[PDB]
Amino acid sequence: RGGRLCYCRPRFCVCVGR
């Protein structure tokens, strides 16, 4: 696909993929 970024870490965390 174009890009799927999804993850979550107590240091930083965000989900986005489109």
Image (cartoon, rainbow, N blue to C red):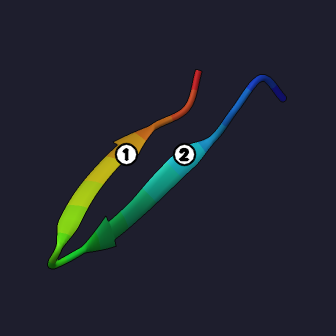
Q: Quadrant of the C terminus?
A: top right
Query: Are the two marked residues, 2 and 1, in contact with CB atoms closer than 8 angstroms?
Result: yes
Mark 2 or mark 1: whose residue is earlier in sequence: 2
Say what secondary structure mark 1 lies in: strand
Q: Amino acid at mark 2?
A: Leu
Q: How far from the left and from the top, in percent, is residue 7?
A: 42, 63
Placement of the N terminus among the 4 image quadrants:
top right
Residue found at the far front of this picture: 11
**17 is higher (above) or lower (below) than 4:** above
Disc 2 secondary structure class: strand
Could you say which quadrant of the image residue 12 lies in? bottom left
Say the numbered circle drawn on residue 2: none
Q: Residue placed at 70% from the left, 32% from the top?
A: 3
Q: Which mark is residue 5?
A: 2
Q: Which residue is mark 1?
A: 15
Q: CA distance from mark 2 to mark 1?
A: 6 Å
Q: Report the residue that reaches farthest toward the bottom.
A: 10
Q: In the shown orientation, is residue 14 left or right of residue 3? A: left
Instruction: Tell me if 15 is positioned left or right of 6 in this view.
Output: left
Q: Vertical placement of 3 versus 6: above or below? A: above
- Could you tell me which residue is drawn at 77 percent across and 23 percent down? 2
Q: Residue at x 37, y 45 (%)?
A: 15
State the image coordinates of residue 4 (x, y, percent, origin top left): 63, 40
User: Residue 10's spot in the image, x, y percent?
Assistant: 15, 79
Residue displayed at 55% across by 32% down: 17
User: In screen coordinates, is 1 left or right of 14?
Assistant: right
Query: Dot 1, crowdedness within 10 Å: few (<14), some or many (≥20)?
Result: few
Q: Amino acid at mark 1?
A: Cys
Asked if 18 appears above or below 6 in the picture, the reply is above
- The percent coordinates of residue 6 (x first, y second) are 47, 53
Q: Is residue 9 left or right of residue 7?
A: left
